[PDB]
C-alpha cells in the first residue's frame, strides 16, 4: 500500500484529488489483505515447514522453566531411528548389559538401576535449581538497601508521601500544610528530582497517601476532601473545590474516615480507615458505582498511635500488603512488615544498615543526629522488582529528604542512568575537596585556559612571567569562570595575604582555535582596604612617581617620599588616579589629612607631560 | 437577513497538516502488519503447536483406528503407544527392577524405559538451554537506551559524525564549516568528552562520514577530497592538500562522489555513493590495488533526499548494516533500520522512549525542542555488544550534544566508570540545588571550616559570638572557597538585605592539623553603595565617634545622631569616610557635606591615643 | 482584492465531517483485523489441516523413502504402513527392551546401554559446568580494572597503606612523617574518602603496614614500635607511647624488625620482616602468648631493595598471598605476583591499561607524566571477591591519590552506590564546561530563577526589558548563587566589555511560590576601574546631568559639556556621586583635575529641587 503523503496545501486541485486517490488505494489494500488471510487459513499449498511447529510431551501446565516441548522434525527423526534400530540390532547377553549400566558417573556400584538414575537426576536437578532460584527470587530479608537520589522541597515541613508516574517518569511529594485546617501540598519533580511546580489543596488532611488512576494517557488523583472522593488532574494553579465535581462515595464507609491508596500500575485501589482495616477494591467497579470487597487485614494498636509507634508508610502489590513502623529513632527502631491478603504476617526487618554521611549505620552516624522514615512505594517495571523507602534527614528547620531502594539483581541500572543524566560531569575541584595545581612550566597566564580552580606554588609563581608587578613573590590563586560558547573564558586572579591586601584582576581570553584569533582583554582592578597600608619600593618605579601606571590604590609612611620628584613633604600620602579619558590621560590626585600643612595635589599626567602641581 | 460568509484559505493549514500526519500513521500500520505476517509465514520459530492441527485419515489407516478426523497430538500419541506396545509381546515381563525403573520423576506410569528416559532428558535440556540463551540475546527492539555522556564543541553548528579509538579510548567528532566550499573540522576529545585539539580540512564536502585504518599501532583516516582518497594521520595542524598524498581510487567509482566508513576493528571498509548503494570492500585490497565487491545494499529514495527524510549517519558490522532516518520531530520520527548483506530488511525502531531533561519521552519534554538525531556507531569490545546513537539538542546557535547506547545485559559498567573518572565527587551544594545548613551548636566563626556553600538562619544568626557588629541582626550567608594544598580555605561573608545594601568580607584561615597551627588573617572589605546609606547608632559606638574601627564604610547619615557625638551643632548628618589606613592605627578620616548652605571638609589624623583637630 | 482565495463556510465544513468518519472507520478495521490475527496465533482450534505442511527429509530418512521433500500426510501414511509390517523377535529374556533403549537423543545407535548413558550425561554436564563456572570464576589475569574513587590527605607526602573498617565502612590511610627518625600519620575518612581527623605516631618507622583486630565491637591497631607490639585504639589525640601499655612481642622474633598486616576479617595476621620471609600467625594465639608458625613464603631479594625493584605494598588472603613490584614507570613496570602458601609462584600481571585523565592506559597520558604504585588490600564482603590497587599521581609537592579495583562479576554495585552518596547531583554546567544558554523567548529578567550559571547573547538583550541603562547593547552574563531554604536566589550581572568595564550588579529575588509574594531587591553596585573611563551620552539622559541616579560611575568627555546645566568649562569635567542619605537624596560632585583651571562643584540633588554649584 503506497499512499501519497506530502500533499500540497496551497494548490486547490492537487489536495482535493489526492484525498480520493489515497482512500481508493486504502480500500483496495484492505480487501487484498483479507483475501490473503482467508487463503492462508484454508488451502495455501506450502503454509508451514515442520521446524516451526512445537510438540508438547505430556500436558501438566506450561511452566516457564520446565518445558516438555520438542520440534516436530526432531521427533520424526527419533521415530525413524528407533524403528531402524529395532530392525538392525544384534541382541546379546542380558546379565552383561545389566551389570555395566549400574555404574554411575563417579564410579561407585549400585545394585539397582533405579538408584543410579535417581542419584544422577537429583544431582542435576539441584544444580539447575540453585541457578534458577538465584535468577528470579525476590527475598527481602537478604537484600542490602542502596542509595538512589534525593527530592527537592519548598519549605521546612517534612514530606509524607511520594509516588512515581509511569508515563512521564516524574515523581510527586506531599507536604503538610501549616494552616488551621490541615491541608497538603503537591509538587512536580523531574525524573532526577528537581522542582517545577505546586498545587495547594486546603482542608485535605495531613496527607498520608492518595489514589492514582490513569485515563487516556493522563493521571487523576483520588482524595477524600469534605466527604467527597473527587477525581481531578494536576495544574499549576491554586485550590480545588469539591462541590464542582461529583463524588463517587461508597455507601458502606461514608461516615468513617478513609484514605485511598493505589498500586504502581493504578488498577487496584485500597482504602485505609480509622479502625485500622485495609480493604482491596477495583477502580472500574468504583466507577460503575458498585461496592466490592476482596480481602482485608487488621493491624494492632501498638503500631497505630504516635505515642507507642507512629503510623508511617503503606504499600500495595498484587498479592501482598506492606506496612512500616514508627519513630525510627534509636527507640521504636523503624521496621517494615509484610502481610498476605489472608491475614498473615511473613517477615520483618529492622532499618539499621543504611548509608549516611559518615559511615553506614544508625542515626548516630549522620546529620544532626535526627533521622526518620516518611513513606513507602513499590513498583515493578520492565520485569524487575524494586521497593522504595523514604527518609527525612536533617534538623529542625533544616530538613532534607532521601530515598532508598531494595532490589532484585537487575536493579536500578536504569535508575543510575537517570541520576547520571542530571549530574555535574566536568570536574571543577578534585574529589578530595582540594584545588587543581598548575602543570610544570607555565610561562604566560594565557596558556592556562581550563574550566575550574587553580592554585599555584610560590616557587613557580616566580617562574611566571608576564604578570602584574604587585603580584610578585607571594603565592597566586587562579579561578577561571565557566565559559563562552566559543570556549572563551574569564580569568580571575587573587593574592594570598594574611596581612596586607587581596586584589582581583579580571580579563577575557579569546583562544581562537577555529576561526577567531588570539586576544587578551584589558585588566580590571577591584577596590578594597585592610588594616595595613601599601608600602612602596622606589627602585621598582624608577623614582619618577608618574611611572605609577597601575589603576586606584593607597600609600603610607614618611622617606620613600624623600626620593620623589614632587613636593618635598616629609610625610607620605596615597597615589590615586581618579579617571581616564581617551588618550591615556589619568587624573592623578594626592592628599594630606591633618592641618599641619593641609594640601591636596592634582594634575593631568599625560603620557608625555605633567601640568603644574597646585591646590 | 443573514448573508452568506466566506473565509480565506489560509485558515485551513492545521487541518491539512493533520490529514498528512494521519495518512503517515495509516501507512505505518500497514507496513508493520505486513512485516509481522511475512515473519510469521517463514522464519518464526514457535508458530503453532500440535493441538491446533487436524488430520484426515485415508483408507488404510481407517482399518486401524476406524475414525476419520483426529488432531495431530492424539494421532502421534497413538502411534507411539502402538510402537511401544509391540515390543512387550516379544519379552517375558517377569523382571521387577525394570518395572520399578519405568516410573519418571513426577510419578508417571510409562510403557517402556524409552518414555521415561526421553521425557526426563528433554525436561532438563529445555531449562538448561533457556538459561544459556538468556545471556546471548541481542535484539534491538527489546533494549531500552541509557544516557552516557556529553560531547564538546568549538562552534555553534551541529556535529555530524563520531567514533571511538580502540587504542586510547578517545573520541573524534566532525563539524561542518560555514565556508562557501564545504569543509569540515576534526576534533580530538578526552575519554569523557572534553576538548583537546583541532584540524581544518577545507573543501572536503559536507563530512557526513569517514573511514578508519590502523598502521603499526597508529590511526589513519581516508577521505575523498578533490578526487583523492588520501591516507593520513592526525595532528594539531591546519590545511591538508591532495598534492602531497598518493591516491588509491579504483576506476569503477572514480567519477562518482562518495565517502567511506569502517568497522570498529577497521579491517573492512565500505563505500556509500550518491546512487544510494552501499558496498563492501577490504582495506588490504585497496592498499595493494585490488578491487573486490562482496555484497551490496540499495536503499529507497524517500530516506535519501532532504525533501522526504534526510540522511544522518551509518554504521556497519560483520553481518548487519545499520541505516538511520530523518528529522526526528513529532513528525518524521527518527528511526533506525537494521539490514542484512543479502538485501533484506529486518526490524525498525522508533526513537521516542529516550530520557530527556524535563521528562521521559520525545520532544515535548526535551528542551527548546529540536532534538535532531545525528549519528551512529557500532562497536563490540571485550565480549560485550553495544550500539551508540547521537543527538543534537537546543535551538539556533544554542546547541548541545548527548550520547545514548543500547547494550547487552552487562556491557556498560566500563563506560559508566570511565565517565565517573572525570566527574565531580565533592558536594559543593546539595542535590536539589539548596545550600548546606549550619550544624547545630555553632558559636565560633572559625569552626565552620568545610568546603561548600552555607546559609545561616536569622534566629540563631546572632547566637554566634564572633561577628562584626555591622553584620549583626539579619540573616547571613557563608561561601567557603575550595581549598589549599594544606587544607587551608578562604572564607567569605555576605549579608542578606533587601533594601539597604550587601557587604563582603574575606580573610585567610589556617586549620593547623599536622604541623602548622591555628591562624586567622585580617579582614578585607570592598565598597558598595545604594539608594539608602547605613544608619549610625549613638548607643552602639559608645558615642566616641572615634570608636569606628571598620574600614571604608561610607557609613553615614542622619541629622540628632550628630548632637550626641563630639562634633558640635552640625544640624545635618555628615558622612564618615576613611581615605587610607596609614599603617599601625593611623587613619585618614574625612567627614563632609553635600552642597553648600555652608560647604566644608573636616579632616584629621586619628592617632592611637589622641587626635589633632579639624580644619577646612 | 488581488490576493486571497475564498471558500464558502457551509460547504467546507462538510468536507471535514466527511474525512473524520472515514478515519474512524479505518481505525475500526485495524482493530478487527488485529483481533482475528491474535486469536488465530494462539487459541484457534483448527488452524490448518495436515495437507498444507511441508517436511524436509534428513540424511537417514532419504535411505528409507528415497525422496527429499514430502507432505506431512504422505509421510504419515508411509510410517503407518511400515509400522504394521514390523515383526520383531521372540527371545524369552527382557533383552529386547534394552536393545530398544540404545537410541540416544541425536539418533545415533550405540552398542550397549552404557554408551548412551555416558554420552547424554556428558553432553548435558559440559554445558552445566560451563555456566556454573562462569559465575564464581575469579581469574585475576582476566579481570579488568575500574576506577572507584579518590582519597584525601594532609601534606605533600605520598600515602603508603590503606585499609577499610568492616563495621562503619570507613577508610584509613597512612602518610610517612618527614622527621629524622621516621614516623607515620593515620587519617580517618568518610565512607567515600573525605577527611575527618588525624593522629601522629612518632618514631614508628616508615608506616608501610599495620595490624587490625576487632574486640567487642571496637577497633584496635597493632604496630611494632621500640621492639614492642602494644594494642591501642583510635582517639582524637596525638603521640603514642609504648611505656604505659603491655606488649605482646613474641620471644622468637626479638632481634629482627617486623611489620604486621591483617586480613579483612582480622582473625589472622602475618609478619613481614626485614629478611623478607612472611609467617602466618593467629591473633587469638598472641592474645594468649603462644608462638605458632603455619606457613612461610620466600621472596626473591630482587624485589626487596631500592636499587633494582622497590617494594610497594602487600596483601594476604585465607588461601593465597599477593605481592607488587617497583617504580611502575616505563622502566620497572609495576607488576603483581601471586603466591600460594606451599610457596609457589603462579601468575604475572602488568599494569599498563589503567584509566588516566587523557588516556586508556600508559603514563604518557597521565598527570604531570608521573605516577607510581602505592598499595594493596584484598577483601571479600557479602560474598564478592574484590581486590583494590592504589595509585599516587603527580610530581614534586603536587601529589594526587587514586584507587583502582579488580572485582568479581557483579560486585561493585554497592561501592558505586557508596560513591554516588557523596557525589554531585545538581547540574551547574554542561559536561564540556559550557554555560547554560538563556531560554528562547525571554522577556523579563526576574523570570529566570534557576540555580547555575547563565550566558546570554546580545540578541536576547535586545528584547530583554528589565535591565538598567548602562548595560545596553552588550553581551551579558548571569550567575546565580545556590539557594535559600525557601528557594530564593541571588543574581549577579556582569557586562562583557573587553575594552571598558566589568560592571557588576546584585539583587535578591523572592519567588513566593507557596505563601510569600513575588518581590525584587535593589541593585547594589560594586566599584572598580580599568584603563578607560566610560563616555556619557547626552541624548540618553535627556540632557539633565542631575538626572543620573546610578551609584560611583566615573564619566568624562571634553563635547557633551554644553548640553548640561554646568556652563562654559570647555573641558570634560568628571562625575562621581558620593552618597545617598535616608530620604533618597544624593550628593553629586563634578570635578576638574587640572589646575590650569581647578575647581570642585558639589550640589545637593534632592528629589524635586537642586541647590547651587559651589566651590
Image: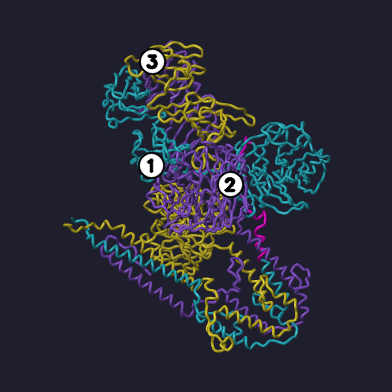
Chain colours: A purple, B yellow, C cyan
Residue under label 1, please give it. Answer: C457
When the figure is inspected, residue C525 is found, relative to residue C454, above or below; the finding is above
Q: Secondary structure at mark 1?
A: loop
**Dot 1, crowdedness within 10 Å: few (<14), some or many (≥20)?**
some
Q: Write the residue at 31% across / 59% down.
A: B15
Q: Is residue C128 left or right of residue B559?
A: right
Question: Rounded to the nearest whole Å, what is the CA distance between mark 1 and mark 3?
Answer: 47 Å
Labels 3 and 2 touching (C-beta < 8 A): no
Labels 1 and 2 touching (C-beta < 8 A): no
Residue under label 2, please give it. Answer: A301
Q: Position of residue A236 (x, y in %)?
A: 40, 46
Q: Quadrant of the N terminus of chain A?
A: bottom left
Q: Quadrant of the C terminus of chain A?
A: top left
**Dot 2, crowdedness within 10 Å: few (<14), some or many (≥20)?**
few
Q: Depth check: give the residue in front, A152 or A205.
A: A205
Q: Secondary structure at mark 2?
A: helix
Is residue C246 covered in magenta? no
In the rendered structure, find residue B601 and report the number of the disc placed on it.
3
Span highlighted in magenta in the image: C127-156
Let me know if marks 1 and 2 both belong to one chain.
no
Let me know if marks 3 and 2 both belong to one chain.
no
Chain ID for label 1? C
Q: Position of residue C379 (x, y in %)?
A: 68, 48
Question: Rounded to the nearest whole Å, what is the CA distance between mark 3 and mark 2?
Answer: 81 Å
Q: Position of residue C18 (x, y in %)?
A: 30, 65
What residue occupies the far left of the structure in this picture? B1
Chain ID for label 3? B
Amino acid at each position: 500500500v503506497e499512499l501519497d503523503k506530502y500533499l500540497p496545501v496551497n494548490r486547490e486541485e492537487a489536495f482535493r484529488n489526492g484525498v480520493n486517490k489515497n482512500f481508493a488505494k486504502i480500500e483496495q489494500g484492505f480487501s487484498q489483505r483479507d483475501a490473503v488471510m482467508n487463503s492462508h487459513q484454508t488451502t495455501q499449498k506450502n503454509a508451514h515447514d515442520t521446524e516451526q511447529i512445537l510438540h508438547y510431551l505430556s500436558d501438566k501446565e506450561k511452566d516457564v522453566y520446565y518445558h516438555s516441548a520438542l520440534d516436530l522434525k526432531h521427533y520424526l527423526l527419533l521415530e525413524c531411528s528407533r524403528i531402524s534400530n529395532l530392525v538392525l540390532g544384534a541382541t546379546t547377553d542380558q546379565s552383561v548389559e545389566l551389570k555395566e549400566s549400574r555404574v554411575d558417573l563417579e564410579g561407585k556400584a549400585h545394585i539397582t538401576l533405579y538408584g543410579r538414575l535417581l542419584a544422577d537426576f537429583t544431582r542435576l536437578k539441584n544444580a539447575l535449581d540453585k541457578l534458577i532460584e538465584l535468577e528470579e527470587s525476590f527475598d527481602i530479608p537478604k537484600i542490602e538497601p542502596q542509595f538512589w537520589t534525593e527530592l527537592g522541597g519548598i519549605r521546612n515541613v517534612v514530606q509524607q508521601y511520594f509516588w512515581i508516574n509511569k508515563l512521564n517518569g516524574r515523581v510527586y511529594q506531599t507536604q503538610s500544610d501549616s494552616q488551621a485546617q490541615e491541608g497538603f501540598y503537591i509538587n512536580e519533580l523531574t525524573p532526577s528530582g528537581h522542582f517545577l511546580g505546586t498545587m495547594h489543596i486546603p482542608k485535605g488532611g495531613h496527607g498520608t497517601s492518595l489514589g492514582v488512576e490513569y485515563v487516556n494517557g493522563q493521571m487523576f488523583m483520588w482524595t477524600n476532601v469534605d466527604k467527597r472522593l473527587v477525581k481531578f488532574t494536576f495544574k499549576a494553579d491554586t485550590k480545588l473545590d469539591a462541590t464542582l465535581l461529583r463524588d463517587y462515595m461508597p455507601s458502606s464507609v461514608a461516615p468513617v474516615f478513609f484514605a485511598p491508596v493505589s498500586d504502581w500500575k493504578g488498577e487496584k485501589m485500597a482504602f485505609r480507615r480509622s479502625d485500622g482495616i485495609i480493604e482491596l477494591r477495583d477502580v472500574n467497579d468504583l466507577n460503575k458505582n458498585i461496592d466490592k470487597v476482596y480481602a482485608q487485614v487488621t493491624i494492632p494498636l501498638e503500631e497505630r498511635e504516635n505515642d507507642y509507634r507512629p503510623m508511617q508508610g503503606v504499600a500495595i502489590s498484587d498479592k501482598n500488603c506492606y506496612w512500616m513502623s514508627g519513630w525510627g529513632t534509636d527507640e521504636n527502631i523503624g521496621k517494615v512488615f509484610v502481610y498476605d491478603w489472608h491475614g498473615k504476617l511473613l517477615d520483618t526487618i529492622t532499618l539499621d544498615n543504611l548509608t549516611q554521611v559518615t559511615g553506614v549505620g544508625g542515626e548516630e552516624y549522620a546529620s544532626d543526629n535526627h533521622s526518620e522514615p516518611e513513606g513507602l512505594f513499590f513498583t515493578e517495571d520492565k520485569g524487575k522488582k524494586v521497593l522504595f523507602v523514604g527518609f527525612s534527614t536533617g534538623g529542625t528547620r533544616k530538613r532534607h529528604h532521601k530515598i532508598y531502594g531494595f532490589s532484585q539483581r537487575g536493579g536500578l541500572e536504569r535508575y543510575s542512568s537517570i541520576v547520571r543524566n542530571g549530574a555535574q560531569n566536568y570536574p571543577l575541584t578534585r574529589g578530595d575537596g582540594k584545588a587543581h595545581s598548575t602543570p610544570d612550566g607555565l610561562t604566560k597566564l594565557s596558556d592556562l585556559t581550563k574550566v575550574g580552580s587553580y592554585y599555584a606554588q610560590g616557587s613557580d609563581v616566580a617562574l611566571l612571567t608576564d604578570l602584574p608587578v604587585e603580584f610578585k613573590g607571594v603565592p597566586l590563586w587562579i579561578d577561571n569562570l565557566p565559559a563562552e560558547q566559543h570556549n572563551d573564558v574569564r580569568q580571575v586572579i587573587t593574592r594570598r595575604s594574611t596581612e596586607k591586601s587581596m586584589l582581583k584582576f579580571e580579563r577575557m581570553i579569546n583562544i581562537g582555535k577555529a576561526e577567531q584569533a588570539f586576544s587578551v582583554g584589558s585588566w580590571t582592578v577591584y577596590q578594597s582596604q585592610t588594616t595595613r597600608g601599601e608600602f612602596i619600593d622606589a627602585s621598582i618605579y624608577q623614582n619618577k612617581l608618574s611611572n605609577i601606571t597601575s589603576p586606584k590604590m593607597y600609600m603610607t609612611a614618611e622617606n620613600l617620599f624623600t626620593d620623589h620628584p614632587v613636593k618635598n613633604g616629609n610625610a607620605g600620602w596615597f597615589y590615586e588616579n581618579s579617571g581616564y579619558g581617551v588618550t591615556g590621560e589619568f587624573r592623578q590626585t594626592i592628599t594630606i589629612n591633618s592641618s599641619l600643612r593641609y594640601e591636596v595635589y592634582s594634575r593631568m599626567v599625560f603620557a608625555d607631560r605633567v601640568s603644574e602641581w597646585f591646590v
